[PDB]
Length: 221
Image (cartoon, rainbow, N blue to C red; front, top):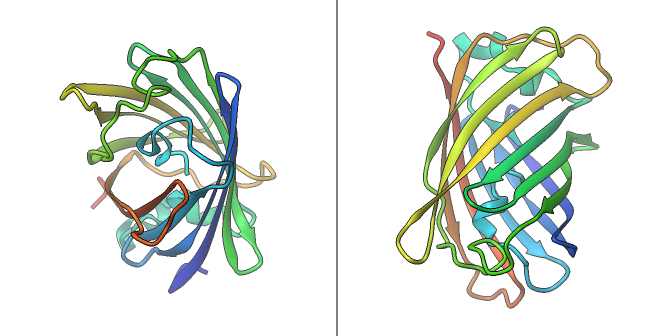
């Protein structure tokens, strides 16, 4: 199921300050190397928010988990029925992102269907005003188990590059719960390291983003 290359489909429907938009992405994932190759397309015209603010929202089941940490891989253990990924993202001196996604297998394709909602964003801010650089700094995240909520939690921050040279933080509050509320693997505390590369397709005329992502788990010998 995750031994070789798995095709990926991402569907995002959301709106920020009432500005509706949709994003569709296609690609493939390689969990053996924690590698992800995707191409996202804004199917409603121009994206009202910068692409770097949607990378974390747009599939941790493809993260590289070494053998000694296979007993702590919640994302793969919930497959193929899948899990739910809820997030509350708070942007520094700006609005909030509220997302809910379902990551499961629909046939031979790993599907991530998301619903986003941004509340009370400044129309002249860095988000709605498109003042961020086309980059995403590397970051780590602490993963902990939630025996009471029958899932896992994760709180981490992202450093976004502003075009004026400054740095804007985005506090992420993540919660994952298996689809169906069935028996869940409770992992020990560990870390997830991410590396992202954002580029453009020289033949694509629509608003899009090409992404090369590398996710690796660590913290348990």
